[PDB]
Image: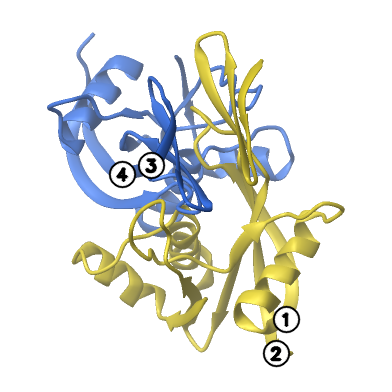
Chain colours: A blue, B yellow
Amino acid sequence: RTYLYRGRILNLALEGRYEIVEHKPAVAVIALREGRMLFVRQMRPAVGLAPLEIPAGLIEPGEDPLEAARRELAEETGLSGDLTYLFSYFVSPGFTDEKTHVFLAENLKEVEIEVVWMRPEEALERHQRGEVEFSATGLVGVLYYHAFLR
Amino acid sequence: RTYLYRGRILNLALEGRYEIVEHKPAVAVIALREGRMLFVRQMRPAVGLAPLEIPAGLIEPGEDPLEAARRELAEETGLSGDLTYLFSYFVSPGFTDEKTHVFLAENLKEVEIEVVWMRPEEALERHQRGEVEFSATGLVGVLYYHAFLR
């Protein structure tokens, strides 16, 4: 485990042959209201475009997944709600250890990037038409809705 | 766009403040047979464990997504089938440009890591119990099934 770079949100290391990118764990929040899902968009220099995502972010020091989920929902959309843990996933285990914890938010209330309320059916259609790209969190939100929230 | 490292499956660059990891695009194949989903597991040094994934891999030079999907299904499970493009997603647009193209495989036939046939319902239950971890591809497969393949 030799380190080649120790950065802000990532570290680049080598385990002999394998190139490993260490990354802080993250959270994502799925929220549905009046048939619309709470998506967010922001310029992502890594991809050169703004994909359709759901409220998400990195877990800060001293914070657990649930707390980070609450914070991200508030900071990105100005909302708070009753959160329930759903599941987790490694974004790309072939090279990074980033693990994302997904939560469901209910009974939303306004307590205070681009907020994009959109019916998941429309988000899926737009994507199929090539009009918009998805982040893993955005796609997971869309699929989760079609599977359990209809 | 300053490069700090040019590796095998990734490049580490900087766009002033943003740390960007360039990565080859990938493919993932969702396949269902007799109610069981085709999962695969392999040791992932990046995470130190073997998460539940679906046949997947990097697109090779001169190959398009569909062709890579065919190859990965054959190389990892020894199967071939009729493939249909479903959707795509950026694994983590906050730092990497890795884009995954997801396909559905039908009418599987044996033409020639660990092959794990499992009912998606069981995969979800095991995960909820903390018995197994999911890769983004594995979770997407599970959610897609519950949403459109039941």
* Element at label 1: strand
| Residue that sits furthest to the left in the current view | A62
Quarter assignment of residue A34 = top left
Does A84 appear above or below B130? above
The residue positioned 49% from the left and 63% from the top of the image is: B141
Counting from the top left corner in percent of width and height, residue B43 is at 42, 66
Q: Position of residue B110 (x, y in %)?
A: 69, 91
Q: Do dots 3 and 2 share one subunit?
A: no
Q: CA distance from mark 4 to mark 3?
A: 13 Å
| Residue occupying the point 15% across, 35% down | A64
Q: In this figure, which residue is indicated by the disc labeled 2?
A: B109
Q: Which residue is mark 4?
A: A102
Secondary element at image label 4: strand
Looking at numbered disc 1 in the image, what kind of residue is underneath it? Ser
Do callouts 4 and 1 point to residues on the same chain? no
Q: Which mark is residue B38?
A: none
Q: Which residue is mark 3?
A: A98
Q: Residues within 10 Å of mark 4 (few under 14, many from 20)?
A: many
Evaluate if marks 2 and 1 touch, with contact meaning CB atoms under 8 Å apart: yes
Q: Residues at marks 4 and 3, common chain?
A: yes
Question: Badge 2: how crowded within 10 Å, few (<14), some, or many (20+)?
Answer: few
Q: Which residue is denoted by mark 1 in the rendering?
A: B80
Which residue is painted at 33% across and 57% down in the image?
B48
